[PDB]
View 1 (cartoon, rainbow, N blue to C red):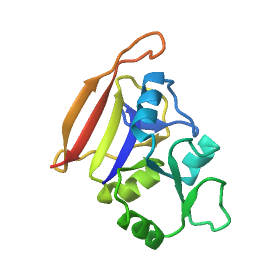
View 2: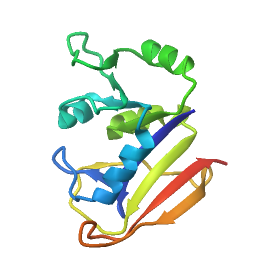
View 3: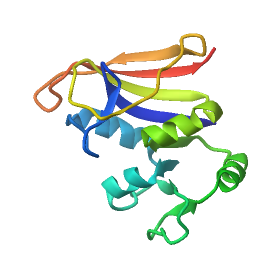
View 4: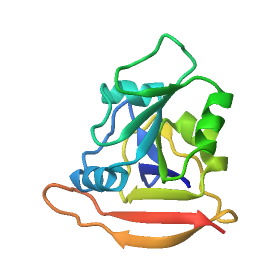
Length: 161
């Protein structure tokens, strides 16, 4: 199936000035372990902030510009190209970002891996609302606050009701 994977704070902030306002190694390691060997799908801003394809993942970028063609990535330019690509999928695919792409794909996704950080940070981009009428928690794992991870957090998995 197709899944969203995202880290957000108490107010659903997912970014500030194209960067993350927090640093949580535990979440980066979780993201890496979960996405390893799988396709990750991201918008242009997300790819740009990363700068290069993530190793061990099949990197996919969704942007319209046909001149945008970073090395080591599949680029999907239209709603038709994205659906056809989605239609052939068999393994779990991860949409990793861009509030815009998260919004565009919410309807074809059946699972959300949400890392909730229990703190508030400056933010200018947010993950959309998760409807209680549409989603329900199927897994919840408290995270470990320590010297490397300065905030309480939790790894949550939602699936459709």
